[PDB]
Image: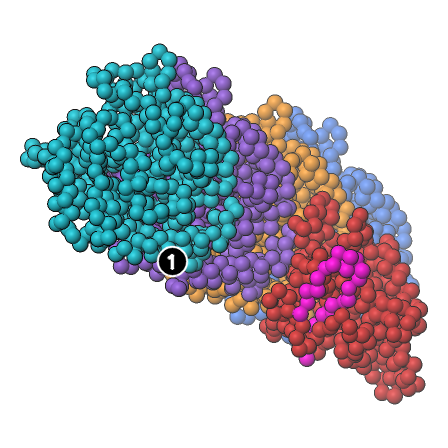
Chain colours: A purple, B blue, C orange, D cyan, E red
Amino acid sequence: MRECISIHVGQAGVQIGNACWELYCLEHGIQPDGQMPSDKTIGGGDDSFNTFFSETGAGKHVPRAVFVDLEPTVIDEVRTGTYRQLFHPEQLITGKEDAANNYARGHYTIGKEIIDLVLDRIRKLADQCTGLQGFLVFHSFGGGTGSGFTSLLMERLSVDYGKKSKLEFSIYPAPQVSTAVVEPYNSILTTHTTLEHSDCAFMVDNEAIYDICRRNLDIERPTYTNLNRLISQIVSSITASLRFDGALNVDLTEFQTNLVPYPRIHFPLATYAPVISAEKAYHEQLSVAEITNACFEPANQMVKCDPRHGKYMACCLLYRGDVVPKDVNAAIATIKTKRSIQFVDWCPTGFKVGINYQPPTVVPGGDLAKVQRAVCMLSNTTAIAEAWARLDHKFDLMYAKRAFVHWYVGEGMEEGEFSEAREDMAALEKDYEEVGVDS
Amino acid sequence: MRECISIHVGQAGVQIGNACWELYCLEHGIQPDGQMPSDKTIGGGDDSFNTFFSETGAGKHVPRAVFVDLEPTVIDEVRTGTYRQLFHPEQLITGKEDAANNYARGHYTIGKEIIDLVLDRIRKLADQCTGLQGFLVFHSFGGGTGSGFTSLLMERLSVDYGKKSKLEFSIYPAPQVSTAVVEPYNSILTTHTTLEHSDCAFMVDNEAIYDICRRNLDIERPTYTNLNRLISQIVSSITASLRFDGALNVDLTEFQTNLVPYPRIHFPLATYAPVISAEKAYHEQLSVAEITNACFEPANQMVKCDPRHGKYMACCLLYRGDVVPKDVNAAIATIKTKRSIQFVDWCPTGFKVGINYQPPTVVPGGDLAKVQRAVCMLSNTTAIAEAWARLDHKFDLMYAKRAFVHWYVGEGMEEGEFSEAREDMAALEKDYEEVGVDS
Amino acid sequence: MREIVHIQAGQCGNQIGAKFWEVISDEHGIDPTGSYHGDSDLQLERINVYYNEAAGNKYVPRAILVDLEPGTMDSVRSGPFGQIFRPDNFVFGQSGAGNNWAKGHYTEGAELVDSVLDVVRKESESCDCLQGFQLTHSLGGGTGSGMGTLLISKIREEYPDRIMNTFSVVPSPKVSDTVVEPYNATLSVHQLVENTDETYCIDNEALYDICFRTLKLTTPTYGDLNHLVSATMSGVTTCLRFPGQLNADLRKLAVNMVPFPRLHFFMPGFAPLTSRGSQQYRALTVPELTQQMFDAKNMMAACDPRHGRYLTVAAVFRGRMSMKEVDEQMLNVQNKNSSYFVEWIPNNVKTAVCDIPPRGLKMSATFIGNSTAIQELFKRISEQFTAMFRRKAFLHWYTGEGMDEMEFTEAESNMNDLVSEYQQYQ
Amino acid sequence: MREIVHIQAGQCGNQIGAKFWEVISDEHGIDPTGSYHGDSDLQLERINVYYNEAAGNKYVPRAILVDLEPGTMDSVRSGPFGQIFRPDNFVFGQSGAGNNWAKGHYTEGAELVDSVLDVVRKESESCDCLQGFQLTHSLGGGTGSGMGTLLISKIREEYPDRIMNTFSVVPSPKVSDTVVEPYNATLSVHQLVENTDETYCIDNEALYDICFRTLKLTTPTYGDLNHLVSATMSGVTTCLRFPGQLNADLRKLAVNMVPFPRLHFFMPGFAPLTSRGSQQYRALTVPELTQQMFDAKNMMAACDPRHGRYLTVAAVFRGRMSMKEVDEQMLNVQNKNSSYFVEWIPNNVKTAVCDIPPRGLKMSATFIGNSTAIQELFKRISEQFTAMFRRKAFLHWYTGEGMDEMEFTEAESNMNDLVSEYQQYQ
Amino acid sequence: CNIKVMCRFRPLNESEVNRGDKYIAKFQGEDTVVIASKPYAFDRVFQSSTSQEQVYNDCAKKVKDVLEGYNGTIFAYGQTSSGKTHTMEGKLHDPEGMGIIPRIVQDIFNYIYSMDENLEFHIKVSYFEIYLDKIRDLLDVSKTNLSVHEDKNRVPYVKGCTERFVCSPDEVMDTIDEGKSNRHVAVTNMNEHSSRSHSIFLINVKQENTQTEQKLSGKLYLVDLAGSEKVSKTGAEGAVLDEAKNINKSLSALGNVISALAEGSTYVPYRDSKMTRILQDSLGGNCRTTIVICCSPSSYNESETKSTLLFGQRAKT
Ligand SMILES: [Mg+2]
């Protein structure tokens, strides 16, 4: 019942968002041209949707977005598509040039000309809200906008505002599939950002989601417009308890002191089920004791690392739909006993259930089934410490011959700002090494 | 599309020219009495022919010639023939006496009375042109006008104008056939001219052209009016790219820095094919890969020396007609492999193609066939160093008894001006000896 | 926005361009007359990357046609799509050039360089924030090489940051057609290397192969070689001009493809390429494209890349793909040839996807390779030079315009170093 | 007279209460709207123990609903029996609480404690001589534990003598639903022990048992767990509100059941409890009640009392009994288990009898036990703490609001002592 | 061996003690410097106490062999107020107060006043800076935008540079000062003026003997580097930024030259950075080069001096 603002950086950002918002405007009845076919407006308190919208006059609803990219080319598809009328045409910022996968070029040299126009449409929005929960910062570790420009937007947003909850959904370099020869510089370079100036960093790779689309959804020729919808329903559920009545609610601050065992160790890796096709539905009567079991298969982790080799340190399970709160207990019961699902000792409690009442919602022409239950684990673990290690063996080579250094030092940075990032993805690794040893 | 002036000296000159111009005025549609049957003269730039003509009034075209001879007897056949109306009756210079195969008599004593009237109709013509390319200086090493008078005209034209391209087509003494007992004095005497004051010197002997008329053209009783037409089409092709659209053009300056490996070594020896009869035509379907092969037979060299005994140092191949520029490449391919066609090493590049679109044109009552392709190699070589050697063994005798010296020293020259010319055709020989040795 | 200007110089440059601007013009629905008859509102959306507005709804391109012989500039004007260049743009001297590099870099061009350097500025300030200069020119003739390189080193002093292209047709021994290539070329390259940030080496031997074997033509007039180099150029910049699902511009490619400052001599290629007697016997989806694309006989640059290793590679696709096709095909052809891709750089293949095809087709891909194989292109040249110069052959026609003898050695050393420093990565 | 006030704090407290005040309200014949439609003049005789008069014959209860998230206070208001709380009574901050005990005892509640401490006084002076504060609240969440304990230690300084209740739902491992229970709980209990005189420990594991096994329900929504803790609460105070043949009030039980100052952690229970498919196969007179009542599977508090000994026990009956039934049943079940009742206290069972049943039934009994078995309830908690704290896990979210590290050790020691001093009597 | 690096930590002023910057160094041996638990390995390093003349006694004595017949060069690197201008220019008029440049020029006049009369030597200077990627002269205000070309033997120089003979110290230093007076714009509103552009100083000594008609030459380069500069902590904008962008792409590219030489690879990237091309001979095999980096141990400059070391840490392995 309270509100949270969203930022999108980079074009993977913007296009994750296109689907995000086509879904939100469907969960609440908000047509493409801003209206919700209305009633006699009798009231005394009426905040059915407010968390992702704002009412203005005569019946129009306007979303709270900050779409930002230096590439001037992706936003235009917005500005003339079927979502023309709806956004507020003074939010979608659009620079002049693009950083071209050069990190140093989104930090200062091509981005010093847009922060002052985007901090402004933040602050004109952080004050049309009565009380503010959090900042959802969608971006993409891959390219260049989403690595420098975000490391600028987040630092500004963390010394001006300072103490808010700043979430972060971010696409990570895969281990094999890639589309940029200079990715392992960007990544190691944005690590100083996703430690000092954020709290939850939900990473999501790509080959993983590709699998999750080929094995389960019976679609073998996917596109980006079918990975983004899954990364969209993770977000319609981590923020599904601010927005509907619940039988056991969990609020975007409860999440963190349930989910973060220390100041730094805060990189959970999400999951979601049921993801079933249109005809592989009726052969399943998928009741709760099943969909809580799909979440721990090391073949639905949206981040390609093996959770078996590791140890969980927390969990969080935001069921939703037609779920009554005993079945969940027998379910967590079954899970608590298994071998090869090794919870660490110092967290014998284990879990944090949370339920809602609204069925997860469908998007026409989509590729998911009208299920009546759902779940999105957000399970901190130690296994993720074996994805970042990969990018290290992709950087301690492309840097031993200073390859591609010139494009970077060319726009201000120095040769040191690389070894800093080295040691600072080395400490993170040492620390998930540590907090997993048993005492 | 730019213009070049022509000089004719000596009577072999004038009669080479008679056919030259009967052909030019046919390539463009210029009737004998100066007119080209015309149109509505709508324009905005119209230079279809200009390179060998100049438009004047009411539709008349006047050529750019300087016909010069001290003999007053050959020009008159012009001045009353069928080419009466057309030339400009103030160009055809005509002196009083003739030099009578006495070189000293065309240099000063009988020629000091015509240079000042011929330099003038040069300069009134070098300034009715917008930009000027070159001077074609037709003459004849044989007689006396064409050896002294030209060595005067060229020196004047080389210190007044100085830096232009000055070409030179010149008939050479044959090794056996001759018609002057005092030829081997003239020749060795004009060598100081065709080194310091010219660039291309296309020599053409006579017995050679006689062969080329008896073996190929099926005419056994030729005349001068059938050697001159072949020496005319060499010139309608070395200047066939200034004058028509081309698929790969070569301009009268490109020629030289393609074709002249040093400052002095610039005596190429031309060639031409197809030369086929009227009935020996249909048994040939002479496509490009054939007519590029006729050019290297040591039996179509228009200068009777053996190219086999020698080494090429450049080439140039100005194809014309219906020739597309791949066939030429397979053709030059075949030629590049053969034994007994020895290109020197230090020019591994080899060739310089060049193509045009206008079929070579026929002259009624002539003796060539309406072919649809043509080619005129201009191949610098080292073999030519074995023609000049001949004239040396025809001068180191007629000078050991000072024979015929009296007619020469009689008109000013001295006994030394002979030994100068000796050493200066000795150095040229030493230098083609040199540039052929492999390093 | 993101505007590109265009410089042509030489008979090549111009006959390439008069076809270029026919493919570009028919992508965006532009008639010859400058008018417009598109059908989809997507064409006219970035029209201002290669065009300018002019009253009454005419569109006129941003050409700067240059050469030293006033015949070419007339041949262009009468062809189809000739009414369109607006006539001030041409700049023609009137004395030819004569396959002598000197006369393009010191004497007969130095007095024409300003009447073009003074149309770039006229055409560099009707644009919001431009991105780069293209420069399409044959590296063999006399205008192209010398005049063009001079033009380029003047452009890189009034604009020391914008990006710089070159589409340079290179000498080849088996279809050579001049006798002083090995002076023209090795003099041009000592100055392309210091003053551009990308150079697509087309060359005519290979471009002939690609029309004998693959496209199976009886007779390749030049009109069907230029019509392939045109499509590579149209490709390398298709994200600036259409909406895409992973956008890449000249800056993208020029940062992902150049692994050091100097090694920027790419080789292009295009696929599909079907003799349209053979077309019904092959239906291409993505993998057919990506397998033709890496063939030894679709490198428009004459060399066999198997004797070398791709340092980096780019692939700019056009059409509706399904992006895992792209990603997994690239991983496939990266793991099948583990010995042809250099090790100490992982994930060598940069990709991109546009969304409108070239009209008439449904899928197309423009490969841009950067291989160490070019070790051989500049190598044979050096032979055909280190013999000729070793006897000062043909030399005088150069000393006559001002150059020194020393300058040749400078070029030579500076194109032997380069080969040395592809050779380390072999 | 003998009036009781009522404090709810947390999502629990409120959803318990909205059912509480439905059982209470239908005992006394109260409609939702505050009006009255009883039938027997006995109902409206002590109506003023849980109610207040308001003009026009409306009756409005004495609730103080409290929580830090403004959703609950709306859910209450729309339910059945919601029109009834008079609206000034709610007190809601607007920033949630976040399962962090700190934010309920120092920061985000310390600025809401007064707008409730200033409605207790408004609701503590419309009464002649009141008797105590109830406080129904879940010991696991963030409002309940910290905010509620703060409220309680403020109430026990402006009223150092009146009696103090608490109905605290306790953590259980087999149905745990948060990750920082073992901080919430052990911090709450270090302050319930010093500042209340009776505490009924309900807990959710056992309350689920009692609806799987005994009441034989397919599906226990929360609406049928709260509907049992409501009946225990309605019981423990039924003599204040009806005529009886041996009356017992909160003071009675709180003097007969607490054998030292600290040991006041009772466990409740209720009987009959019949799956009303099974109801016609059992007719209960007194002995059936008193045998179900002492079953290991009707201790709403999760522990097996057989591993412990009842120190003292109370039984508040309702219905028309024949009192020797009561007395001799109690002597019976005191001599059958001579090893489960502590020796050095004789006649352990306090009894009482009301006279009106809960409507629809004819006989009912509310057991209140005080066993040393609770030795285990606080014991397992300590494990789930002495591992977590031993690695400062989850600790920062507490230091961030003011608490010290030391304060945790204080709590720990002070909930290990307690177990030691039930353990002597074992 | 081939290459040698030198670090020198100046002592502390009164502004630091007023602000009370802590002392942050730690040493050990004569090789290891350590700041904040990170080890830096070097060759030769100097405390707050070591005196000026041992600096050059261990740094530039083996200049002797420039005059005796081979090539040489010395870089100097330094952020603001880190002793650069104190360890090179130095107290000009104390025998025990001068810096490094005069500690060279004096050895050269000594060698020329103490050698036999059968031998004759020539002393030559040149002074040019690099700025925004154009090689500017200093001794000639208007000769700007030079280029570079080689000879037949593949050793480069600058085509047009003003060269003035030199025979006396005053001549040397007079040139030095007149050149200094015309580096491009340098000083700010605060005190971050740290030589916005590089500078190069060539000292040519040629020798010839008449006993044996043997003629030798030695080129001696003095390089004054500019200061690396980040683009957050500074906050620059507009024109000054174009300076930043450039300085770096030199130094970082320079890095590679100093790497593969010391490493030992097959071929070395000399072309990509106009300065390394001017030196190309003076760094390589059978040539002696040494870097002279200057670093402050105070705290208000902390995140600076870290970098001031990593650069040098390159030139070792
Ligand atoms: Mg040309």
Judged from the image, the secondary structure of the residue bearing numbered disc 1 is: loop
State the residue at coordinates (70%, 78%).
Answer: E286
Q: Disc 1 designates what residue?
A: D387
Residue E275 x/y as whole percent = 73, 62
From what the image shows, is residue A280 above or below residue D58?
below
User: Which image quadrant: the N terminus of chain C?
Assistant: top right
Q: Nearer the viewer, residue A183 or A39?
A: A39
Query: Horizontal placement of A79 versus D60: left or right?
Result: right
Q: Is residue D4 left or right of residue E210?
A: left
Magenta-colored span: E1-26
Q: Position of residue A89 (x, y in %)?
A: 54, 28
In the rendered image, the residue lying farthest to the left is: D281
The percent coordinates of residue C66 (x first, y second) are 67, 43
Q: Is residue A34 magenta?
A: no
**Going by the image, does A258 lie left or right of C19?**
left
Residue placed at 86% from the left, 77% from the top? Answer: E108
Please tell me whether residue E57 is drawn above or below residue D408 in the rendered image. below
- The amino acid beneath tag 1 is Ala
Q: Can the viewer see residue D35?
A: yes
Query: Residue at 40% across / 61% down in the picture?
Result: A436
Q: Is residue E23 magenta?
A: yes
Q: Chain of mark 1?
A: D
Q: Bin the neighbour count of mark 1 within 10 Å (Cα to Cα): few under 14, some 14-19, many 20 and up.
A: some
